[PDB]
Image (cartoon, rainbow over the protein chains, first blue to last red):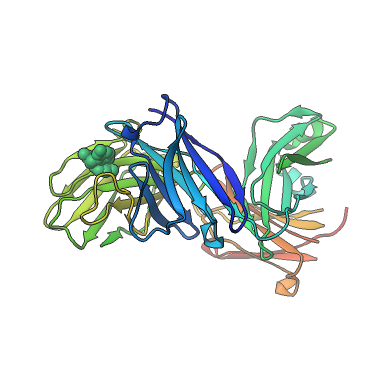
Length: 209
Length: 201
Ligand SMILES: COc1ccc2c3c1O[C@H]1C(=O)CC[C@@]4(O)[C@@H](C2)N(C)CC[C@]314
């Protein structure tokens, strides 16, 4: 089908105005796409915000408004509040079927930016005695809670055997995540260096063994 | 309006399970039920639509043959049969409804059920291997099912500790924790409770 594209993440501050966008892979977003918006708050609390491009649903605050901007649909929050921190999904109708966008995580800032604290652990002796080797990359104290992880072996980019957790909130309202690189014992011995690289707010923090 | 969904479900690959969503309130109108899929590592995905009063349906091409939507007017209930289950079918499935006497151009996702969790696995109960990490840490690898519990030095060590969510490696779950010296791991499903201390290399 068509593919619907949203920002992966966006940042705003209390009282600011932020616009979220929702693009269609087929061309301009038309009024015949009848653009919907859905807000997801923690614990699967969903609220239908917008129908028919710009009809705000009963009960939804007036600061929410939908519209078309150029060739795409959009959701504008005029005077963002703390409670507006959520994931916003858009959805487009293509005559006989519906497609959701990937969603946009909206952070409403409540503390200064914080870069990820990164630690990388080697496989233990006892794990190697099963002829397996797991490299553990712990990532903590970053804000906003959005990170990309990339691994390397002797400088070359790794493409297989990586598992990474969704960023989860800390008690100090910063975020944490973990990434695991799973190998055989021999494969870990073959190489001189392994590295975990975290991308956050346009900057990379990296650790190597 | 209320949408009551069926209970959580556990299945083996290739099997089939049937979910249900009972609507309450203003069911004299003919209304749409939209089904939605959300995996733990994904956003929302539209499965299809069904009107329980008129039986009409709209489908997502990707789910034709995977999901079948049916309904019955008098009980105000919609069903979704999921066939030939796989790991990608593990998700929370939501049913949704439009507003009462709303327009077609109003928001379609007004009322939401509590969601039905579907987990597809061939894994038998497996106790976690626990490994020291050297800030220091504790690696909890290869258990099933969730959950596990982890503390540090019987719970006397709590500040400066980060315990990360579980992840699925090789059809089993793997977890980790770290501290700025021993970790206590409990896997009730395997009736296990292991302790491991970090002797330096
Ligand atoms: C312009 O009208 C519409 C545009 C888009 C959709 C609909 C419209 O009217 C309804 C219709 O005819 C059948 C399809 C569908 O049930 C569906 C999608 N749902 C989600 C909402 C209601 C409705």
